[PDB]
Image (cartoon, rainbow, N blue to C red):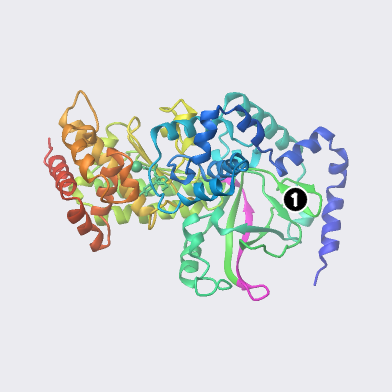
Amino acid sequence: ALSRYEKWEKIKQHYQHWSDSLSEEGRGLLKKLQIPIEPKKDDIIHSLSQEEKELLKRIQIDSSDFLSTEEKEFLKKLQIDIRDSLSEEEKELLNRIQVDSSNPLSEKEKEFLKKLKLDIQPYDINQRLQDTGGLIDSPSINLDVRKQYKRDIQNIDALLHQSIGSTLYNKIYLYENMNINNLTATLGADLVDSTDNTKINRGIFNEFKKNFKYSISSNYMIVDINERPALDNERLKWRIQLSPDTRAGYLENGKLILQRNIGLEIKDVQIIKQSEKEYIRIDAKVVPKSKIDTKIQEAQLNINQEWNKALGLPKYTKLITFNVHNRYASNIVESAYLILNEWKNNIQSDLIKKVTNYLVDGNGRFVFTDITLPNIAEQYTHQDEIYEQVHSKGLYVPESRSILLHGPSKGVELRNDSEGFIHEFGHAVDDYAGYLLDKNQSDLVTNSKKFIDIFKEEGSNLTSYGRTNEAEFFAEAFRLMHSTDHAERLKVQKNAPKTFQFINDQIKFIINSLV
Ligand SMILES: Cc1cc(S(=O)(=O)N(Cc2ccc(CN)cc2)[C@H](C)C(=O)NO)ccc1F
Ligand SMILES: [Zn+2]
């Protein structure tokens, strides 16, 4: 055994001059990176009108279809403060109406929350870096805050000037404990076996290992000099080897902060045992970011050439985009091949071809990303207003004729990423149908005389989320009609006959469009 405390001491000495040279502005900066600054709950609540308090008190927050997971969590802690001023029956009653309460929000509820989200952003450098993938000019937060982020990130980059060096880099390992849900909320919930939680589901594991070949860090990784025993939710244990010129800084209690924008090549992925629980070891080696970007671009070129051919498109149509910057990079890239495969397997070749030609005619894109959708230009160039921007698993944006699919998050009511894609392709089918109906006044076919009536009657029969509005109802019905599960296709035909009819009609109408 090679001594944890001597390893520590030697890395501390390597950075001792650097540490002692830090101004205390420098020190403040590093602590702020480590410990984000949260919103002041009191002030938020103090600023609500009495009518807004009453609303926030009674509102069900997971009914939202646009808030991030971070925003959703904060709001719930905010509901609590609001509520601790009540009777025990009030509190119990208000929680009593929560069981059969999967329903869509009222319009005055949604409008309120959409504006409230501008006021509950933490100031959190590493989160801002990961969310935007390093592209911090993205107009998804207030301009003034955005500029404060830029100054801080620039100053941190300038503090991290000293590399680990030629002597240390192949003598030490660095460690990082991770929650599986921070890479894939989908595989996360089902990689710990259900029979036994101390075991790893070998099938999912082979899937995860399958193309986990590279990884990108767009923020500043905090790593441990010595391995720390896992917490509850920490089933991923990274062991990282740096490169000689990897720049880093010493943090107290045996940590290193690494420079942003590095690449990691996955060298090995194993199941290992640590006190009768199973964990996943991930061995990784720091490489230059550009190397991995080169691999991403070649994959993008190759998936487009493959799909340009299969779709009867010009050879150099830029159709599929990899917008990839985060720790599960290579899976995003590989997952897109499989998603597009399930798409061609479950939808008529003529429908797919005629609609995708329409998207390409409007300079459209299939964007596969691991940054948040508000930070994708296919959304933000057409949605100036932050209160109108959407976080979700998937989005169709008609103004840019693009489908956006966010890899890392897990969609409610979804079995996988392929299902999510097909629902988005449902919005695009709705778009083209409305255009064919009326080529100058290009509107959505769900905004038509007919379909509104159909929705007013059958709008409650299918999925809970189908009850939101005409657009979503259509999209869900379209998704269920092309499910791999046979039973799903028929429940639509039986529980909502007119919609079934109406969609199959539009599909006919589209395929029957020509030269
Ligand atoms: C069920 C489902 C969800 C999504 S989604 O999660 O990506 N999504 C909506 C959303 C629904 C439900 C909830 C919480 N119950 C939150 C958000 C977005 C806005 C959407 O309508 N894109 O067209 C995509 C495909 C799906 F089949
Ligand atoms: Zn939708």
Magenta residues, dominant SS class: strand
Residue 493, given in percent of the width and then of the height, sits at: 17, 54
Query: Is residue 171 rendered magenta in the image?
Result: no
Tell me: residue 111, above or below residue 210. Answer: above
In the rendered image, is residue 123 in sight?
A: no
The residue at 62%/28% (across/down) is: 145
Q: Give the SS element for disc 1.
A: strand
Q: Residue at x 83, y 67 (%)?
A: 3
Circle 1: residue type: Leu
Q: Which image quarter: residue 354? A: top left
Does 241 sit above or below residue 515?
below
Q: Position of residue 351 (x, y in %)?
A: 20, 46
Residue for badge 1: 256
**Residue 288 located within the stretch drawn in magenta:** yes
Residue 143 higher or lower than 417, as above or below = above
Q: How many marks?
A: 1
Q: Picture coordinates of residue 102 (x, y %)?
A: 40, 49
Identify the image quadrant of residue 84.
Answer: top right
| Residue 433 visible in the current orientation | yes
What residue sits 80% from the left and 72% below the top?
1
Task: State left or right for residue 324 relative to residue 486.
Answer: right
Question: Which quadrant, please, contains the C terminus?
Answer: top left
Q: Which residues are magenta?
A: 272-290
